[PDB]
Image 1 (cartoon, one colour):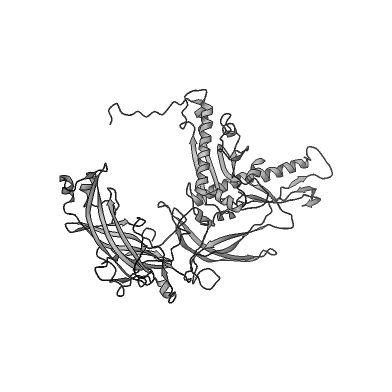
Image 2: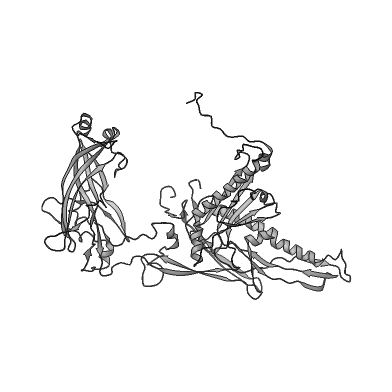
Length: 570
Length: 52
């Protein structure tokens, strides 16, 4: 009895209606369109839920105002580094796809215009932008390119020079108040596992690096920039081999035999650099992110089911040949609540197994083949595992075997439940759909008459974990042979909701009594034609197969000890 | 399948049927393979070498 109520809670329907509708309101963020309404610009453009962003980082990130140098061959190739040392780089900015590159160090007496290099196709397409455009209040170096060369072989190193406490432009005391100046004095060091823009460790310094040494390069770069106009320039001033340090972090001479031997043949030069500049749009020029909402209609309605037809003789009333109507009622209860519940639960299990696979979650709103409106909140996830009590048991006393096996099973249940909570983030969804409070998720257990005397521990009580609410359900089913089924239920209220597992449609059905002749045989009839159905909402449910319990309790098991080869084998 | 991919078919089926005489019709309008998902719910282009 309690099994169906726990897994498919009852919803009553007056025989006036056929069902109820579920109108769900969600919020979207997206980019680019036409007009003010409708979805997309010319064809369909995708959206995703914002609550999915609580678990990710790339779906709510914004980059639509930064100034990135953009190539136009034959118009601005002069200031870009020669594309024979490092090829062009494809970056993504807003909606435009284009190639960028590091800017050349301005040799003595030459300048560049920064706002002439910022024309992404969107800014060009959208007309001539605001002329009162001013550069960002903070300007700093992003990357610096150095080229260590040994016998004509070039290896490139892209060092993250950003955030270093001198790589930020500072206001000057001098000339116009818009001349935004920069002076960068420090020594940058290359460690032993230091990455390469071409990947892995460079072969040029491998012999030195293995010997346990790190090198510091003194960087000497100066430049200036107007924070309003765009004309500017910056030149490297020096790069030299300054110091070498050992694994112990002590100063070792550059004249030492080993160090000088390893440093022979090295030449270091500066090639280019990158500038992190942003537009300070006093006037609006960006369509950025959006906030939009749409409603989805789902149709739920309740069928009828074949009549459990009862025939009795007429012209007499009896006690044996006329069984009680109580037999009718009990048969109806059995049909309603036992066969169908288990068969539909098993169908859902196999359906989720086919649609989602084992241990493989999917993003929110990724498919509609699964059923229920629960898809709109939780990540589609199904998981299962097996426990072999014979081989997964190590007990040191024959008196503590049963407590040990209950501990094993409880630990397995705990682990899988917490893993599902991690991978699905159901708590966040329950917080969102239920504002003002955080009812802790409940855990429902579906089991036959065996494990209730193993799942329940008569010692330590952690059957589903600390700080959970749980209900254990026992059924006399045989298809539930040594199965346990786990999923989450809401024990509050009695109305359909995308988070509750499932609701059974139920329209009350009343009998008819009448004298009926059919092919000239005359008798009395009793009829019940039920109207009910099982529906599934929440796409989260876990099952465990338990096996070999009785062999495990019948045979002794003693330890899995790993003999470690002091007897020669290694 | 072994690579770890499931296919999805987009389908639009329309039909009408009468609950008074039992007359009705149904016909298929759209049926084609459109999308191939990865081990995630992230779209995989049909132009990549393996799937293509």
